[PDB]
């Protein structure tokens, strides 16, 4: 087709869905390069695609491991049209747990994938859009990049780190015609969190009884939030899509006004003391 | 003495000035574990402290490299007292430039030192505090951790990573007696050509030039920053943030005013590039 979109992190969730929405889109507009970290895990994208009947050629998958800077370089050359209209930054990793119980390897893959991963991504793909003076970069936000969430500290820094990188490049990209937009999402129903929790034992050995106590409390709180407010991957799909569509795009797109109030309280209290109060209260009463 | 403080990056700047000020406080109450990356760079500290009259024993130095879990562990192991009343997470690194011009290694070091290094201290030190149900963590934050800066993306992400990381413990730690705080700072005294394209190149150079003017306009002294740390340190109800200046408050308030990030991007693009 004609608008060339490239998405990172597609064997499931937001990537998968964002991918097949676009490949299936009726106006047959974009050609979607669904990249997966490990190509062996692609059957789900494929059925998805068939399930919505993406016309043949509207979608190609590639292997892209955001950890691997050659892997990135590699994907790129495999893009036939010699351009990327919209480049969607989506690969992520979660990390839930008492600060002092997280593995060193794990704090480093979260920041490698979440932060270094978007960095390596944008580095490979931004240059050429700057040249053409046209280009669109979409980056999956998280409420956790705007406000701090008990027991998700490392995850929070990466989401927070992502707004640091983005609003920073946004100021420089203005005049190029390359538009950067983070897509902040609240809880999305994808099993991003299924991949996230060690077991009681781990937690147990790893931390104090008190803290061990606060974690299940959050855990039970979060679940309830989840079950009461998560959106579907297809909903969020639609949000990249609109921002994607918009002719003069803002820096942020909300997938929900859900947390809006709370994001305001923050902004309204610079000592950051009020927000802490609430969160604390809302999470542990 | 009694308030045992452990502080990172102290051979120069805020670490040096915070380390000694404390050691020489007139209430002769803090014990200062000033730690450095290379002990072969510790003259000024000792010189400062010697020149400042510090109670014999009030100051000591350990070799910590926040990039090394094992180096973090031993420093910890060297705190004879057995508690840590004030842990000062201060070690940081800048990284500047055209993003597509930054090397992978520079990028990962700034994330290792600025972000993974505060994770390490915190995990070395918060459990004991939780236990005591007492302990203050002051963290050296930045302005660039508060809002985007052209040609500083990695840095800004590291510093923005700090905020969320600290903002996150701030909520949990509440109940255990521990308090966390970032001393938000402004400027403080103390391959490109090949890797980027023309337009990006000039902006880059335009940015630099203006930026060195503003630093000299803005830059405060370490002496001043340490005074904010100290205030914070005495706050019975110490907030999550403390600011060493109000130059960046307006901009701050702007940013929090338009959630879509649009105004800021404009204001700031404007500010760095006039025209
Ligand atoms: N699930 C939620 O509730 C939620 C909320 C807001 C934002 N997010 C963000 O959305 C994105 C996708 O999350 P999801 O909910 O779809 O979870 P998911 O795990 O279902 O999908 C994430 C995708 O990227 C991943 N990925 C991990 N490591 C990778 C690597 N090295 N290279 C390439 N890809 C890698 C996964 O393999 C998967 O393909 C991430 O940025 C996540 O942080 C998720
Ligand atoms: N100076 C400014 O204008 C300014 C602005 C805001 C925030 N900051 C922050 O101040 C902190 C550093 O103070 P500075 O800016 O005066 O820097 P500096 O370069 O003067 O500080 C040097 C000290 O930290 C170093 N260091 C580097 N890696 C280290 C590590 N892994 N462990 C321990 N020490 C390490 C050296 O050992 C030395 O001990 C960082 O958080 C920096 O981001 C400074």
Image: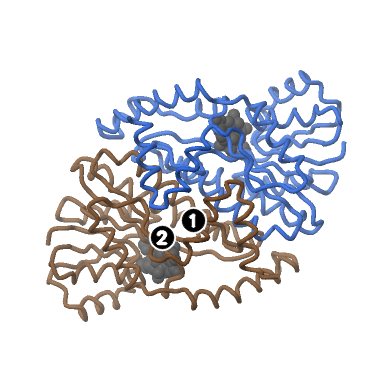
Chain colours: A blue, B brown
Please report, as a chain letter, where disc 1 is located: B
Q: Which mark is residue B184?
A: 2
Please report, as a chain letter, where disc 2 is located: B
- Can residue B191 be seen here? The reply is no
Q: Are marks 2 and 1 in contact (CB under 8 Å)?
A: yes
**Mark 1 secondary-structure assignment:** loop
Front residue of B275/A214: it is B275
* Image quadrant in which you'd find residue A101: top left
Instruction: Single out the residue that lies furthest toward the bottom.
Output: B51
- At horizontal 54% and vertical 56% (from top left) the residue drawn is B254
Query: Where ligand 1 lies, by quadrant?
Result: top right
- Image check: A244 left or right of B221? right
Q: Is the N terminus of chain A in the top left, top right, bottom left or bottom right quadrant?
A: top right
Give coordinates of residue A93: x percent, y percent.
53, 36
- Image check: B133 left or right of A7? left
Give coordinates of residue A94: x percent, y percent.
50, 35
Q: Which mark is residue B146?
A: 1
- At horizontal 73% and vertical 60% (from top left) the residue drawn is A175
């Amino acid at each position: 087709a004609r608008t060339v979109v490239l998405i990172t992190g597609c064997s499931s969730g937001i990537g998968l869905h964002l991918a097949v929405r676009l490949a299936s889109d009726p106006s047959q507009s974009f050609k979607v390069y669904a990249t997966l970290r490990d190509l062996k895990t692609q059957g789900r994208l494929w059925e998805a695609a068939r399930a919505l009947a993406c016309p043949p050629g509207s979608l190609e998958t590639l292997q892209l491991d955001v950890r691997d800077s050659k892997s990135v370089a590699a994907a790129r050359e495999r893009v036939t049209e010699g351009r990327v209209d919209v480049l969607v930054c989506n690969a992520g990793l979660g990390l839930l747990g008492p600060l002092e119980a997280l593995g060193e390897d794990a704090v480093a893959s979260v920041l490698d994938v979440n932060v270094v991963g978007t960095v390596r991504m944008l580095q490979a793909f931004l240059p050429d859009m700057k040249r053409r003076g046209s280009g669109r970069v979409l980056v999956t936000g998280s409420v956790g990049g705007l406000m701090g969430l008990p027991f998700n500290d490392v995850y929070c820094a990466s989401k927070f780190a992502l707004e640091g990188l983005c609003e920073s490049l946004a100021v420089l990209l203005l005049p190029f015609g390359v538009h950067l937009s983070l897509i902040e999402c609240g809880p999305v129903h994808t099993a991003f969190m299924e991949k996230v929790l060690g077991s009681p034992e781990e937690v147990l050995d790893r931390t104090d009884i008190h803290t061990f106590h606060r974690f299940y409390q959050y855990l039970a709180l979060s679940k309830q939030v989840f079950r009461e407010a998560a959106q579907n991957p297809e909903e969020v799909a639609e949000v990249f899509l609109t921002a994607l569509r918009a002719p003069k795009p803002t820096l942020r797109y909300f997938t929900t006004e859900r947390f809006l109030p709370l994001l305001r309280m923050r902004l309204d209290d610079p000592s950051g003391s009020n927000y802490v109060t609430a969160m604390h209260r809302e999470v542990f009463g």
